Length: 165
RNA sequence: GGGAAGUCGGCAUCCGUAACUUCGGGAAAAGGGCUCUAAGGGUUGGGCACGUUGGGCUUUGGGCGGACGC
Ligand SMILES: [Mg+2]
Image 1: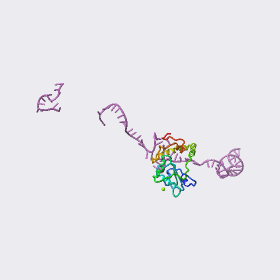
Image 2: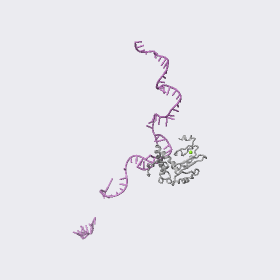
Image 3: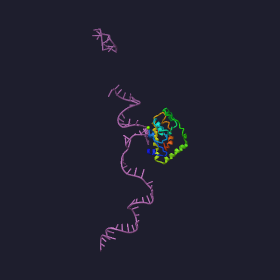
Image 4: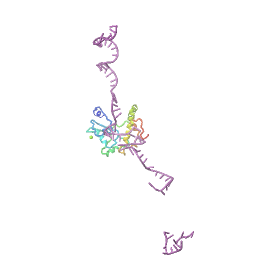
């Protein structure tokens, strides 16, 4: 999987955990998006430098859910690594049209049996990773409206987590 | 009964009632579950057609044997 990345000439995207977050200076790299804010507050800076290297425009953007975890903006401000809001794309969201293209995954989940149990094991794994977030003042499991992550992750049926609804 | 009135000098404590506790196993949700880091039992298993090569289904011929028996 690593070799086919670095040798590919067509536009490519890796889907990775923190494996490629520190050190690897892959060439011709331009874009990073952070689907989940780092659980450790010291790998964001390293992750940004994965897109950068020398002169090249480093498209480093991170998502943030609405709520108190907007404060990740000024958490890094006092990290002395200021982060500004996105301006360059400025194409934000299509709202329901973003929901029904996320729906385009859900019937694919219906079509494919194996992708069914892959879904929650992805969900519970994310549930475990959030519960252990080091900063227990900006990230919290309490104010976590669940039924839109199932919509966000295209989950067919929210499993038997401790929280019941 | 009196009270020095004689003489110098008399003296695992036990039962009932109300809360509390031992042994073993065990970090990292609860009772489908995080990153990285090393081992995570072995053995065997890559499709479909063509003209193509080989022996593999009829046909043709040859050779060695030409035999056995009379
Ligand atoms: Mg380095």
